[PDB]
């Protein structure tokens, strides 16, 4: 080769292609969670709106990485998006615990993207990862921890009054 | 024949006359439910406002069917409106369960009105039933199911805090 | 039961339950009259709008009596609403004469409700009947008398120009 | 072939070409009626404005059918537009009776277009006919019936005061 | 089973689950096309904005079908989303031809969904398909046909002036 | 015749009846041209809007002549409107050339209407023709000549870029 490419390794190009697939898969998991809470035998509307907003954010993360790949001079290759591991999510506390578990994995993958970028002397890539992806994750993790603590203290999962009142007052 | 009548069978004319009576009877059942929740030993004001709104909607359904009957060239015949089957409604969950049971019967009657219109080659009547009466019913049924699920989970009927808080936050 | 009941007889409770049924029956009669004048071989739109307004007023009278019954500490019991005595109303002068005949009967029933209330020493009930129901009746009767006199003088019922011009200028 | 054609029969294509010609012919009949009522020995201005509005509506019906034909992938073929059957329309009641007679024929032709569409498994065409053409006809027929009834009752055609007052108050 | 389910077959439930997957796959194909036209050796910005808008529309179609599935009383099951068949799209006329080919397949699948709903006596489902999905498809097909015709006439693909001027003036 | 007729010959009455038919026929030719350019294998939207505007203007010319016939005291007689001579119009330059050829014929017919009015001593008719119909024609002819010259110079008909750019910039 490209006429705009300068100081961009092949390994970085492969790692960006893996992160794009990971973000699309997370967006699909959140979409499944959202429409579980819309059923007539679950019926909690603010849980549903919350997870639909999360699903709309992961997709913007993916599109931003695709724009970076085109700016630096590499080529995009897409893969299959696999289906989520759960079909029924069982409760409102259980979904929050699974969401925490997923955001920690995404954070762990970004940290290795950053160590690869520093092993190759690519300061533009290091600055991109630090500015756009690293503070957002620790904020999301802190919020999900707060939610899980409050739901455990109110008395869920073996109490429906707890999840009804949490649906009303926090979300 | 009448000078405006064209492609309108006698059987359709009798079935429309039966549906008008069914809508008037449903309006009278909702009016009974409403003023049960206004008594001084029940005293729940948002249950009462909710059922009064439902009562005002059924009467508009009936008047729309009468206008159709006059547009196509048939004649209206009215019958006696019978009294409701219950006098005391016992609880707030119990009334929602009876309301669900009533809306399902009205839906079942509309489906046979539609099969009769199809067996007779009357596309104007089929379009009227599909446009004005069929999506409204499935929406009403989905809402009443949501309400019953939430009230059962909060712990009603053997808990007064549940119905007090449901009166305040949902209705 | 009741904790709010004070100075309220059983006979008064039965008479209020009869007046509620009478008001619902009058509302049903006016609804029949209204949709007779909407047919394509009668076709007089302001007669129809006038009788539809009367039908919407009788129903509010009934709901106000139900609220009184709950305020004083009695219990509501509903009956069957019978069908009207006429199906075809024959003319525009004929319907006005039947309407006058019906309002006089309702007035006669209120006068006996008032004499019962005074025979029992119930001043709250006497004040309710005098304030909300007695001047409205004499005003409605005076108006229907005016209408009948004007229609007879213009030359109805054996003149269509008369009822066309009355539909247009007065109503 | 056409690159956009899918699930569209030749018979449907011929029937749409016949309906276009029928709508153009109806527009020409209404234009003749309009300018009859503008003569100095007839002189009724609101009859004339009413029939000119009807003439402007039939032409839009025809243009909408031509747009459908181009959307589905068929080809338009035009024919001769014949002249109306009457030159002098004789009265104001007589023109309304002829107008009713014409709208009933157009309705009868649309009903066979719909039965052809269902015999061929074309749901897009059935939905087009039901949504845009079938309720409009029954409304037009009900209105013309009202007009004819009122004019007969006022005493037309052997009374000029009747048609003068009807020209002034209804139209 | 469910407490809201009435007149809903198992076969319809399986067919809706297949249509959801088809809509998600179409959205992913459009997203691939969009970011091909953003490369530095292709560089056509209005082609890219056009295909990104199409990608955002398919996802709303899918979410609407999921809401229907929950309203009627069935259960959602998700599958893997496969990757697109092409990686490099070769030209601007070539992408429009592939887009036409895709929309025709989606239309063919909806027509069989409708024939299944008719063979089972489900008028609510038939009305849903006719109102929300069938006119939209024929409009999209007519537009893509227009685009392909204009690009072929201007002289593409063996002329860069053609696609530059089409990028500027139409899109 | 008539009580308002004065200085109006029978020959003038027949010539006005012929001009009305000529204007209706021109309106129908323009309507055919318009919907040829809407097909999916022609696809030029501003040619279509231009010819639809011309079609709406010819009909107003005809209605104005009918009003004059009623003002002077003659009687209107209508004939059959024949179908256009072409079905496929082949190109944009070709349609512009046919339009020029049609407007010249209409002008030639108006000039003989004027010579007839002068041979009969009818100054009101001469003033009508001069004020409302004669400058309009020479302006329309000058415009169509401009269009044909520009299209020939750009390189049509054997160049699609020419007609695409003329569609965009002039119309
Ligand atoms: Fe609270
Ligand atoms: Fe240009």
Image (tube, coloured by chain):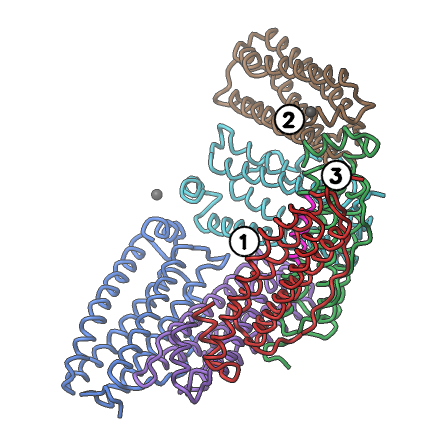
Chain colours: A brown, B green, C red, D purple, E cyan, F blue
Tag count: 3
Q: Are marks 1 and 3 in contact (CB under 8 Å)?
A: no
CA gap, disc 1 and disc 3: 42 Å
Q: Position of residue D115 (x, y in %)?
A: 67, 70
Left or right: E169 with respect to C95? left
Residue A126 vertical placement versus A69 (above, below): above
Q: Disc 3 on helix, strand or loop?
A: helix
Crowding near the residue tagged with mark 2, few <14, some 14–19, many ≥20 C-alpha atoms within 10 Å: some
CA gap, disc 1 and disc 2: 36 Å
Q: Please give the chain letter of the residue carrying mark 3.
A: B
> What residue is shown at x 16% (from left), y 87% (from top)?
F120
From the image, tell me which residue sits under label 1.
Answer: E142
Magenta residues? B50-61
Residue in front for this viewpoint, E107 or B67: B67
Residue D30 vertical placement versus D133 (above, below): below
Residue D101 vertical placement versus E158 (above, below): below
From the image, tell me which residue sits under label 2.
Answer: A54
> What residue is shown at x 62% (from left), y 65% (from top)?
C30
Whether the magenta-drawn stretch holds residue A146 is answered as no
Q: Position of residue E39 (x, y in %)?
A: 51, 29
Tell us which disc is closer to us: 2 or 3: 3
Instruction: Answer yes or no: disc 1 within 8 Å of ligand 2.
Output: no
Residue in front for this viewpoint, F109 or A122: F109
């Amino acid at each position: 080769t490209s006429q705009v490419r300068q100081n961009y390794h092949q390994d970085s190009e492969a790692a960006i292609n893996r992160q794009i697939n990971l973000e699309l898969y997370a967006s699909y998991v959140y979409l499944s969670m959202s429409y579980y809470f819309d059923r007539d035998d679950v019926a909690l509307k603010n849980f549903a709106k919350y997870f639909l907003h999360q699903s709309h954010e992961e997709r913007e993360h993916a599109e931003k990485l695709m724009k970076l790949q085109n700016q630096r001079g590499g080529r995009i290759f897409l893969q299959d998006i696999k289906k989520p591991d759960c079909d029924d999510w069982e409760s409102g506390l259980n979904a929050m615990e699974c969401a925490l578990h997923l955001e920690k994995n995404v954070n762990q993958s970004l940290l290795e993207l950053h160590k690869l970028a520093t092993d190759k002397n690519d300061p533009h890539l290091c600055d991109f990862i630090e500015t756009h992806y690293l503070n957002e994750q620790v904020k999301a993790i802190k919020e999900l921890g707060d939610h899980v603590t409050n739901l455990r203290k109110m008395g869920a999962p073996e109490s429906g009054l707890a999840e009804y009142l949490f649906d009303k007052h926090t979300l």
